[PDB]
Structure formats: structure tokens, C-alpha cells
Image: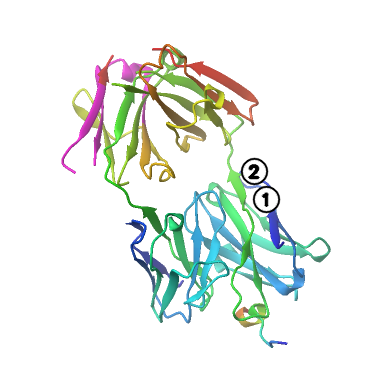
Amino acid sequence: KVQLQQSGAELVKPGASVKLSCKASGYTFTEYIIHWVKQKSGQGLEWIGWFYPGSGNIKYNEKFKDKATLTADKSSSTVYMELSRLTSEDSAVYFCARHEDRNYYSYWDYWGQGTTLTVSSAKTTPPSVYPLAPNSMVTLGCLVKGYFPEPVTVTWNSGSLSSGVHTFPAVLQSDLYTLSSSVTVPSSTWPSETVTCNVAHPASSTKVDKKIVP
Amino acid sequence: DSYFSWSDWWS
Amino acid sequence: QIVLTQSPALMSASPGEKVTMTCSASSSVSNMYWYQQKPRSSPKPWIYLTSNLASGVPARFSGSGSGTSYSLTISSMEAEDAATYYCQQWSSNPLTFGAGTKLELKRADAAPTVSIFPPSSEQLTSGGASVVCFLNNFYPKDINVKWKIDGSERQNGVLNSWTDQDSKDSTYSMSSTLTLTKDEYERHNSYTCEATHSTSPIVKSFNR
């Protein structure tokens, strides 16, 4: 099995540096180039540079000359990318991908799972959870406002209500995240059978339940 | 030997 | 500096339908590479050297083109083929990608289930006031949301959020949130969440 295992997510202050890693296995490390690619918020892809551990040769996109530094450790089958002087512009997912050096008919045949980098001044802030209360089918919801960082877990009746649910992706208000979730239940269910939205924030180690009261 | 190298060709 | 323009940016297809999508180069390129990506997963190689399928890519897929104009084609659309497709060139340094073509499942048109919510007592006691509006299970994705306070519309302090196409329903959902000061909220009476989808505007509203 060919596999490229990348390092876990990273939260860093503006101006600091971070070192992403791409650990390879299942093949001869020295026979394949390792390309690095950038993607912000599931957008388009952007090539940063590559490192070929066969010769030690390196190449950068002119854009990332003074941003990225590629290095490798042959004895651990790992290629590193160091990003310097981080801003909010550098907040993105970063993929590594292998490419057979000595074959013209080579393509980028195996990819890493990706590493999420977040660059922000913000302190860890727990969310304010507010219930949203108002036909044969009724819609409830709850607002999760002013938390940092990502992510949060939103469930309904501790997972019981799976279908009829729409948890939306967060946005940035100032330097904090705001998220919303909706659930649809039959009009005879509610309020007789109480509906509760469960919000959990790992970072601030907070868990909160709000009953939707009419 | 293929006498071909992407790293060399791109360099 | 080679710029790759992928058209259309969005397109839809029913299973069985033929799908062609273009990659256009600002300069000449010797060959084109294509990738498939789906939400919360790394890109997958799809085509290499213009028209050669990557290992495991079904035969219904094909690539074509030369110089400045390349295309990816699906003979017979399948549900699993719904994804974003990117082109890439290796001819000119730096290596550059397209912005993507997003391919969605087609389905019967659907109007949104709109629901509007006043601020919670919990939040009003705090000192803020957010008014939330959900527009759930509509097709196609092309939609517009406008907020009205006592007759006049508002564009300031609004923020929208979209889901991906639903794997069950093939529908889209949106969440629009209008954030006021408690004092601004309580100095107006009627709040309307208007949604246009196009001469039939769905209006849900409340007063304090």
C-alpha cells in the first residue's frame, strides 16, 4: 500500500512560522518528486513547489520563494514545508502529492489527506448557543455565535434526530465564528416531545444543551 | 535507464 | 503566468446525459492534466497527457485538445461523477491550475421552505440581537435573499451560508443571519425575509 501521511491541523499567531510534514511509505522514497499544493476554503488549487529526494533538487513557484522552504529527511521518508511570516492569507489546506521522476508518462498518482493551517490573533472563545423557536411539519433551529477556533459539533436529541437536519458552515464575524443549524419535525411531535440542540466546543472544553421552548 | 528526469527537465 | 479559464464554472446533468467541459489557456501548452475533487477529500488524478485516463478511471471519461483549447468529456453521466474538475499545465513554469468546473446532479425544480426566527430572550438579555432565516431544500442553486425592516430593505450586517448539494434529495439549503444591536432591533416592528428564485418572491416575516 502506497501512502502519504501528512501532519495534523495547526493554529498559529500572525508573524510566526510553522513546519508541515509529508511522511511517505509503500515505495522507494528517492524515485518520486513530492509537490506541495495550496487550497483555501474548498476553492481552486495552487502549486507551491517540489522537492526530489533522489538528487536533493528543489523548485519553487516565484510567488512562494520568500514564504515556503522545502527540506527532507531520507532516513524517515519525510518531506517538510516551512511557512514563514504567516498572515490570514496563508490560512488554507496544504496537500502533498508524489510524481515518478524517471517516467515521462508519470502523473500525480497518490495524494496526502491534507493539513489545515489557521492564522489568527484570536483567543479561545466558547460559543453562545441561542434557541430558534417559531403547517403539518414544523422547523426549529439554534444559533452558535462568537466562538474560536473551529470546529464545533451540533447534534439534535444527542443524534436521535439525524434526517431533516441542515447544519451550515461557519463564517467570520470580526475574529470569531458564527454557525447556524436547522431541524424539521412533524407538528404533532413538538412541543409534546422536547427537541434539544447539543453544541460542543473541544478547544474551550464546553458542552451545552438548549431545549427549543415555544 | 530511461535517461529522462522531471526534476532535471523542469530545473 | 499561464492563466487557465474553465467554462462553465457550474453545470448540471441527469444520469445518461453527455457532459463536455472546456479548459482555455492564455498561451500555448503541450498537454493538459485533469483532477477530480469532492468535498472533504484530497484531489484525485483523472486525465494525464491530454487524453490518457489515470488508473481506475471509468471508460466513459475522455480528454481532447491542443495548443490553447482542451476539453474533458463524459459519454454517459453517473451520480458518482458529481464533483469539481480542475485542469493543470506542466509546459510553462510556474505550474498553474484552472478555477474548476463544478458538475451537479440535475432534478425537478424546488422552491425553498423559508422559516424566519426572532432573536432569543437569552441573546436579548445579553445585549445583542440576531434575526435568523433558513431557506431549505430548493433547486436550482441560483437564489437571492433580501431583508426588509418596516418596509425598507437592509444590506448591512447580513451574512449567508450554503450547504453542498444533498446526497439524498439533490437539493441546496441556505442560512441568512441579520445582526442588529438590541436597541436597533427594538426601535422597529416588522422584519421580513424575502427570497427570489424568477417572478414569484417567497416572503416569511414576523412583528415583535
Q: Residue at x 61, y 32 (%)?
A: A123
Query: Label 2: few (<14), some or many (≥20) within 10 Å?
Result: some
Residue at position x 58%, y 35% in the image:
A149
**Pointer 2 with pointer 1, Cβ within 8 A:** yes
What is the quadrant of the C terminus of chain A in the image?
top left
Instruction: Name the one closer to the observer, C89 or C155.
Output: C89
Q: CA distance from mark 2 to mark 1?
A: 8 Å
Q: Which residue is mark 1?
A: A17
Query: SS of the residue at dot 1?
Result: loop
Q: Nearer the viewer, residue A13 or A1?
A: A1
The quadrant of the picture occupied by the N terminus of chain A is: bottom right
Q: Which residue is mark 2?
A: A12
Residue type, mark 2 in image: Val
Report helix, strand or loop for mark 2: strand
Is residue C24 found left or right of C192 in the rendered image? right
The quarter of the displayed image where residue A83 is located = bottom right
Of residues A191 and C25, the one nearer the viewer is A191
Relative to C41, C70 lies left or right: left
Classify residue C145 by image quadrant. Answer: top left
Q: Which residue occupies the extreme right position in the image?
A: A75
The segment highlighted magenta reads C177-205
Give the number of the disc on residue A33: none
Identity of the amino acid at label 1?
Ser
